């Protein structure tokens, strides 16, 4: 029996007129008579038995006075292994056309973050196979990870590489929540996981979940579909003490979607037009993505930097919540180095001499200081050149370029673009390779060989091969 | 079919004409101003539903309020008055689609403005429809030849992607679109349905005199037979400029869902945002940053996200979008340009400096990029396209050392000269599209270093003479490169030997 | 037909078809004289052109 | 003007009926609207600025 | 007028003046 | 009828009109308040001094109450008296006329009687009009209605009915345009 | 008006030329 | 009949209360009981028989409730050979003290732009005699021209040169429209035109029309004075069919005037305060200035760059409608180069 009824429809905001027993805030309401299942999330009580909600689907086709049913609970999505290896919608509908989703039970997408007494924080190195990352900005298993990048910098391809290297061969499960990104990338990733056997039609397999809130979805859905993916990870965390790998696509779309409707909701725009509740709205999501006594979640979330402006309120507040940070620089891409990981801006909470080995910490700072000195010499070199510099400065610039070029690593996901097969670098070989360069092991050979190589030995063998070739 | 048989079927068709009329609710306008009409009553009206006024002009009910209804006038609002009647049609906004659309010029609503005759079409699709899901889509693996050397080589466009033509005023944004339409005309003549590409040109906020000149060029080259022009001029009401992009997009979905390939070209979207902003501001809605509505990002995203490459299960159709963006002073950090860049796959940056320095098309390859990459290029193109990018990359670096001067190494002199040949090679005039196979030959000669012999000022004329010489004497070679699409070793040896030979035969300036 | 010259039956038949629609929930032009008038002219041309393949 | 949030249907309805029953207007209030974590309460007179209040559920 | 761009160009002139001022000392 | 006005609106005049209709319709009475508010409408337009009184906003609450009492304390439903007292307290006296009119609208919506207007180009003969009544009567056959005539259309020999809020087109002009358009889109 | 790009190009240009000869000696 | 009554007066916006038969939008209304007759164009129907209008003349002296008569038609100005050599007002009134204008018909200043079918290219170069112009941005007769420049950069001086080189030797008629400019130039131009024999009092001469919307006029007048002169040009284009030289002084005032009154009309401000209907309003005026099969109109329009900010919405949107562009730079003037034409910006 429908208690509410449509009264006002403007854009994506829809108001419902209830007769009695108004639904609590965040509750899910089912509109009857719509061609497609439309769900409304209660957000504000305007008085006089009026409630303002946001539509998850296109509001075109609705009609004032259309009956609305009250479920009495927030948007509930199917959880459990049935969602593993299947694409799901913001409201829990399967859009993969593989049939209905089997779930042992339904959990709400809204819940309170775990208390502080039961935080149970822990640090553990995560070998991702990327030498530039494993050295300068090590990742911590169970801690948030941020990939700050602009428009078309290589953050999407980087996420694919982490999945290819981290998701597979993982005892626990994995979740992939793509919010606000283009749909073309979703179809590619689905076919990629299928060919890579990460997902399959045979039940009992596909230890990975996929959630998509692509641009094709209207506002409100892109701001809550992220919670759907989180609920899947929370289920695998609480019910089973298994490490979960949460790969979150660009999250800036979440805060952006809220601002798209914040104006119509009545809120006053912020300094940059964002909603006044940006910190609280974003904080409610970050606090929930954390390790607890039951299980741990290693969340890999990307932050889109609009116009390459890191001073935007959305990403600026995210830095405080992230444990490991990976800031992508556009200048490196111009040079051809990939991944374009900014060595100076990128930081990691694990980069502490007490947490990691002293040798790992020493080699890390040695590279940063080397590059920092080279950056300062660029000014004088532009006018006078490297020749007018002293032998000491010449060696600094020489090794700095070789180390900077050596940071470039070709991965499997970049084969189609570059044409060179991917390569995996271990932590031991990574620290040893750079440590040798810092001591001048490769200062003799040309800098051309220290480009898109996995290990120092590979670069030397390539250098010798070029010699006999000529 | 005999004349008598067709006439009988013609008469029978006219006989079977049905016309049913039902009770339609009507409301009165509380107020009318700036094209916004507040309607009283008119309940049980759907969002975006079409409504007709007393004069006969249509309207779209966007704001459904408990007190009144906010309607937008889809035309001139001089005849509208207080208390006038507003009749709801009962159907969401839609436009006619089909094959008869090709060869005509329509408006935002779809009415033909050419004056030739009424539109003979029976299929009408809704303007705004949910974009395809994730499964219906498919990886882009077909090249969309635009006819431009730099584009087909450095920034390849595959059928089903989204490329952004971003630049300042009078930077060659429209020239790129015209060259593409002209290039696809050849494939339309020859019986290769797998390469036919229907072109759709959406004009938003443009002077009619310019659009008139645009259509004449298409007819001049006979490229209008497969072109569709949607006109939403400045005098047109803001909703028309707001719906014209989605209107033309619906026409493209026809070819998309029918296994065909269609190319839609959205003109400057900043003008759409002004109309969409104007339409939103007049509705008394709270404005966002830069006075634009909060959901302006959803506007372009919903529009461009529809362009995709359908899977073989639905016919293998594809829709390619080429949205255009006009920048004020080359500042891409603005709000609207930044959003569009993040939505589209690749973007073509146009520089005013390169334009006046003789680099036309003024394309900044350093920033331009495409997600599809070499996946769209043909075999004969990927091989040569790879080395071309690397060579150009080095030349841009040594550009500064030229000022330094006072010395030049032997290799640097070669790399500096070699890069100059490529830049001079990639230049192309307006309304002069080139065939895919012809570019392979010219681009091949450049990377190999043969162009380093003759003077730079003579490389452009060599291109014309060289291609003409090949078409006449060496015709089987061109056929292999076209059919097979791969540059075999036998062609490499033959091509590598005739290129230096031809330069010596013809009368050119050989002194480097 | 819109002009004079035996237009009375056109209006008279239209009135009858009009009240028919009003009495019913919807309105359909099954008894309108415009359609048969047009078909008669068209059928005349069909008979005129349909003579023989020659 | 446009409207006053205090002119709710529940409060206006009581006035038209003519019954002067506010259910201990002092020290108690009735929530009229809730949004973005801020709830407006009608009445609740004699409440000091920056003072703590207890809701029906128990939250402060 | 895009303060981010202006502040970058101001930084460049500062370095030029710095290195230019330093070469004067050596001169 | 369920103490629910026909429509719910957030407007100033709409809010009071809706609350009054619900509160009035709640206990027993709707016509009593209807006559009361109607009296204000007639007086608001007939007496000039009364108009300036309501429009006056600089007047004090205590002063407004004394003038309202002088008008009349009886013959007005308690709902109307309580409404006025609320307006004085909320300085909404200026919105009195709109509330009065708005209230009658809801009451007119509850009224079952409706007016049907027929539009025809050619003059309707006395005998012809009789046939129109049987068609409209037989169409509904369950609700009484009043018919009104207005003949100044552009169509020829066409019939167009307006019944409160519904429109049914039986005009010949619609038929002519329909055929001329389909005959053009034959696509022979 | 872009001096930062001028300095940036001069840096990469001279460095490439300088190290290009060093590559020959290294080989 | 005076069916209207002034409801409220707010600057240049005046509302009128009618008993019935409200006027259509853009219709002209005349207030009664006020010297220097005031014309009010209908803009919006606020409801309850209230209509909001814009004032063409100073509103000082109006009284709430004053009667207003409804003409039932938009502002109609006289057109024809009588306007030749005659100065008209935004409302068609002559301000030259020459007597009543002899016009065959009165055309309304509000008209739809020519359709897509009635359009002509007319790609013929127009030699103006200026080497810098003819070299970089050569003007073409029958096309739209745009002069962009800041305060005191040489926009007016350049217009005077074009009139001396092109308008005088021109064969067809001409139309000069001033929008929000110093009245001194209008007087100097009129006397200079008489001295040059380009115009004379003798009937059959003065193949050029003069329209002035000088700054002295209040808002609304500078926003519609262009439509007045434009209607005079459309007459020669359609009826006479001969070539026309439509000289348009600084047009930013039009857009500015709309912004000055937009806020009063209840519109939400734009990005930098302009009106949301800037594009559409300017588009309707720009789409009408075009060549058709009947005749050609070579329009020389000056655009004032506010604060020398070319990125301002007003001038930016104008570039899209112009064929030939000539951007004036103040940096050149400092060097002494005149005309201070920017060759890299004049497209
Ligand atoms: N590749 C080119 N080669 C030679 N001339 C060119 C080229 N591109 C443009 N032109 C010239 O530039 C003018 C038109 O520029 P174009 O329309 O292509 O740029 P636009 O950005 O689309 O302009 P707008 O924004 O006004 O539509 C013409 O004078 C044209 O001849
Ligand atoms: N490390 C990289 N490896 C492979 N391709 C890359 C890399 N970096 C950039 N590309 C280029 O970036 C473009 C794709 O950008 P993308 O990773 O999709 O950004 P986003 O995450 O916002 O979607 C491609 O054109 C591709 O050529
Ligand atoms: N061709 C010119 N040659 C030399 N000086 C000029 C020339 N044109 C203008 N100057 C000077 O430039 C100044 C500004 O020109 P003007 O057209 O009046 O600008 P504005 O559009 O603000 O009226 C003139 O007062 C004049 O003194
Ligand atoms: Mg991405
Ligand atoms: Mg263009
Ligand atoms: Mg001037």
Image (cartoon, coloured by chain):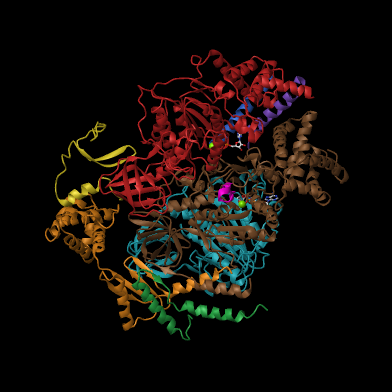
Chain colours: A red, B brown, C green, D yellow, E blue, F orange, G purple, H cyan
Give the image quarter of residue H161.
bottom right
How many numbered tags mark residues here?
A: 0
Q: Position of residue F115 (x, y in %)?
A: 29, 70
Q: Is residue F117 visible?
A: yes
Q: Position of residue A244 (x, y in %)?
A: 46, 28
In this picture, residue B164 sits left or right of residue A296:
right
Ligand 4: image quarter = top right
**Vertical relation: A388 (above or below) F22:** above
Q: Position of residue B72 (x, y in %)?
A: 43, 58
In this picture, residue B268 sits left or right of residue A294:
right
Q: Nearer the viewer, residue A404 or F137?
A: F137
In this picture, residue H135 sits left or right of residue A197:
right
Q: Is residue A331 visible?
A: no
Figure quadrant of the C terminus of chain B: top right
Figure quadrant of the N terminus of chain B: bottom right
**Vertical relation: H70 (above or below) A334:** below
Range of residues picked out in magenta: B310-326
**Vertical relation: B27 (above or below) A253:** below
Residue F11: in magenta span? no
- Residue at position x 70%, y 44% in the image: B359
Q: Nearer the viewer, residue A449 or A202?
A: A202
Give the image quarter of residue A271.
top left
Toward the bottom, the furthest residue is C5
Q: Nearer the viewer, residue A181 or F140?
A: F140
Residue B322: in magenta span? yes
Q: Position of residue A295 (x, y in %)?
A: 41, 25
């Amino acid at each position: 029996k429908a208690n509410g009824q449509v009264s006002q429809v403007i854009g994506a905001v829809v108001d419902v007129q209830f007769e009695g027993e108004l639904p609590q805030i965040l509750n899910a309401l089912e509109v009857q008579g719509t061609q497609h299942r439309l769900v409304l999330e209660v957000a504000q009580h305007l008085g006089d038995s009026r409630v303002r909600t946001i539509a998850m689907d296109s509001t075109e086709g609705l009609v004032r006075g259309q009956p609305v049913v009250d479920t009495g609970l927030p948007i509930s999505v199917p959880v459990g292994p049935g969602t593993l290896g299947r694409i799901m919608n913001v409201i829990g509908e399967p859009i993969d056309q593989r049939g209905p989703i089997k779930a042992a039970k339904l959990y709400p997408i809204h819940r309170d973050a775990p208390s502080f007494t039961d935080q149970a924080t822990s640090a553990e190195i995560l070998v991702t196979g990327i030498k530039v990352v494993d050295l300068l900005a090590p990742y911590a298993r169970g801690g948030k990870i941020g990939l700050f990048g602009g428009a078309g910098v290589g953050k999407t391809v980087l996420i694919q590489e982490l999945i290819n290297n981290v998701a597979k061969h993982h005892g626990g499960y994995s979740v992939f929540a793509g919010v606000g990104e283009r749909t073309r990338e979703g179809n590619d990733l689905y076919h990629e996981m299928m060919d890579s056997k990460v997902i399959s039609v045979k039940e009992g397999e596909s230890r990975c979940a996929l959630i998509f809130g692509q641009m094709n979805e209207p506002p409100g859905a892109r701001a809550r579909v992220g919670l759907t993916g989180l609920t899947v990870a929370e289920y695998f965390r609480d019910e089973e003490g298994k490490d979960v790998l949460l790969f979150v696509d660009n999250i800036f779309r979440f805060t952006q979607a809220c601002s798209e409707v914040s104006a119509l909701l009545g809120r006053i725009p912020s300094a940059v037009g964002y909603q006044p509740t940006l910190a609280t709205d974003l904080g409610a999501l970050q606090e929930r993505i954390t390790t607890t006594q039951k299980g741990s979640i290693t969340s890999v979330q990307a932050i889109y930097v609009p116009a390459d402006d890191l001073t935007d309120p959305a990403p600026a507040t995210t830095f405080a919540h992230l444990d490991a940070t990976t800031v992508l620089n556009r200048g490196l891409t111009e040079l051809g180095i990939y991944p374009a990981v900014d060595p100076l801006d990128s930081t990691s909470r694990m980069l502490d001499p007490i947490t990691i080995g002293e040798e790992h910490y020493t080699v890390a700072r040695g590279v940063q200081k080397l590059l920092q000195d080279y950056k300062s010499l660029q000014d004088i070199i532009a006018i006078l050149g490297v020749d007018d510099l002293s032998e000491e400065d010449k060696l600094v610039v020489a090794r700095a370029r070789k180390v900077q070029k050596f940071l470039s690593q070709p991965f499997f996901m970049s084969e189609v673009f570059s044409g060179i097969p991917g390569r995996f670098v271990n932590l031991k070989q990574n620290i040893a390779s750079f440590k040798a360069l810092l001591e001048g092991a490769g200062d003799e050979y040309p800098e051309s060989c220290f480009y898109m190589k996995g290990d120092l030995e590979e670069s030397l063998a390539a250098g010798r091969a070029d010699a006999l070739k000529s | 079919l005999s004349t008598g048989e067709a006439s009988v079927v013609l008469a029978e068709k006219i006989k079977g004409i049905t016309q049913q009329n039902d009770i339609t609710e009507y409301g009165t306008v509380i107020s009318i101003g700036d094209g916004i009409a507040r309607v009283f009553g008119l309940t049980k009206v759907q969002a975006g539903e079409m409504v007709e006024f007393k004069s006969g002009i249509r309207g779209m009910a966007l704001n459904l309020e408990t007190d009144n209804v906010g309607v937008v006038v889809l035309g001139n609002d001089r005849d509208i008055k207080e208390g006038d009647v507003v009749k709801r049609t009962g159907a969401i906004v839609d436009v006619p689609i089909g094959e008869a659309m090709c060869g005509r010029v329509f408006d935002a609503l779809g009415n033909p403005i050419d004056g030739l005759g009424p539109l003979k079409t029976t299929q009408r699709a809704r303007v705004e429809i949910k974009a395809p899901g994730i499964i219906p889509r498919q990886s882009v693996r077909q090249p969309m030849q635009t006819g431009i050397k730099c584009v087909d080589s450095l920034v390849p466009i595959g059928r089903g992607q989204r490329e952004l033509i971003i630049g300042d005023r009078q930077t060659g944004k429209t020239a790129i679109a015209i060259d593409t339409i002209l290039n696809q005309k050849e494939a339309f003549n020859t019986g290769d349905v797998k390469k036919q590409l229907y072109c759709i040109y959406v004009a938003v906020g443009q002077k009619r005199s310019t659009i008139a000149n645009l259509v004449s060029i298409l007819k001049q080259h006979d490229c209008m037979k497969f072109t569709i022009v949607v006109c939403a001029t400045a005098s047109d009401a803001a909703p028309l400029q707001f719906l014209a992009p989605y209107s033309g997009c619906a026409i493209g979905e026809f070819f998309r869902d029918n296994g065909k390939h269609a190319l839609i070209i959205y003109d400057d979207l900043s003008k759409q945002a002004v109309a969409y902003r104007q339409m939103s501001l007049l509705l008394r809605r709270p404005p966002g940053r830069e006075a634009y509505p909060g959901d302006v990002f959803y506007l372009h995203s919903r529009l461009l996200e529809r362009a995709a490459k359908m899977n073989d299960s639905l016919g293998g159709g594809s829709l390619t979008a080429l949205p255009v963006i006009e920048t004020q002073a080359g500042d891409v950090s603005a709000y609207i340009p930044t959003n569009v860049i993040s939505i589209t796959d690749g973007q073509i940056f146009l520089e005013t400096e390169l334009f006046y320095k003789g680099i036309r098309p003024a394309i900044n390859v350093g920033l331009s990029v495409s997600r599809v990459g070499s996946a769209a290029q043909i075999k004969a193109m990927k091989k040569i396209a790879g080395n071309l990018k690397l060579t150009l990359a080095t030349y841009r670096e040594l550009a500064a050392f030229s000022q330094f001067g006072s010395d030049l190494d032997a290799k640097t002199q070669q790399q500096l000269n070699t890069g100059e040949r490529l830049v001079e090679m990639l230049k192309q005039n307006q309304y002069t599209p080139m065939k895919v196979e012809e570019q392979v030959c010219i681009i091949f000669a450049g990377v190999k270093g043969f162009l380093d012999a003759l003077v730079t000022s003579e490389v452009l004329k060599f291109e014309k003479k060289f291609l003409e010489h090949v078409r006449t004497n060496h015709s089987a070679l061109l056929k292999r490169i076209r059919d097979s699409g791969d540059l075999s070793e036998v062609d490499t040896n033959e091509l590598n030997t005739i290129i230096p030979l031809f330069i010596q035969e013809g009368g050119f300036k050989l002194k480097a | 037909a819109l002009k004079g010259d035996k237009k009375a039956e056109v209006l008279a038949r239209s009135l009858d078809s009009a009240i028919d629609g009003l009495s019913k929930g919807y309105m359909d032009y099954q008894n309108d004289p415009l359609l048969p008038l047009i078909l008669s002219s068209i059928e005349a041309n069909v008979k005129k052109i349909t003579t023989l393949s020659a | 003007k446009k409207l006053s949030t205090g002119e709710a249907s529940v409060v206006l309805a009581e006035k038209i009926k003519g019954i002067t029953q506010q259910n201990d207007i002092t020290e108690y209030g009735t929530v009229i609207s809730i949004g973005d974590g801020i709830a407006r309460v009608f009445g609740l007179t004699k409440v000091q600025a920056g003072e703590m209040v207890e809701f029906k559920s128990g939250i402060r | 007028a895009n303060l981010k761009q202006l502040k970058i160009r101001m930084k460049a002139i500062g370095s030029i003046k710095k290195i230019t001022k330093a070469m004067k000392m050596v001169a | 009828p369920g103490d629910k006005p026909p429509a719910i609106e957030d407007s100033i005049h709409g809010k009071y009109a809706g609350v009054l209709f619900s509160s009035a319709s709640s206990n027993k009475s709707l016509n009593k308040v209807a006559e009361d508010m109607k009296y204000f409408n007639q007086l608001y337009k007939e007496s000039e001094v009364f108009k300036s009184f309501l429009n006056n906003v600089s007047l004090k609450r205590n002063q407004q109450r004394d003038i309202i009492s002088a008008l009349g304390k009886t013959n007005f439903n308690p709902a109307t008296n309580n409404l006025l007292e609320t307006l004085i307290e909320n300085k909404r006296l200026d919105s009195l006329p709109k509330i009065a009119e708005k209230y009658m609208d809801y009451y007119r919506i509850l009224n079952k009687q409706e007016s049907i207007t027929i539009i025809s180009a050619q003059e309707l003969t006395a005998a012809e009009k009789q046939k129109v009544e049987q068609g409209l009567k037989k169409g509904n056959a369950n609700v009484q209605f009043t018919v009104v005539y207005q003949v100044d259309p552009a169509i020829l020999g066409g019939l167009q009915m307006y019944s409160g809020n519904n429109f049914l087109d039986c005009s010949l002009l619609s038929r002519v345009n329909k055929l001329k358009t389909e005959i053009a889109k034959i696509s022979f | 008006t872009r001096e930062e790009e001028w300095l940036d190009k001069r840096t990469k240009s001279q460095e490439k030329v300088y190290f290009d000869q060093e590559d020959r000696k290294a080989m």
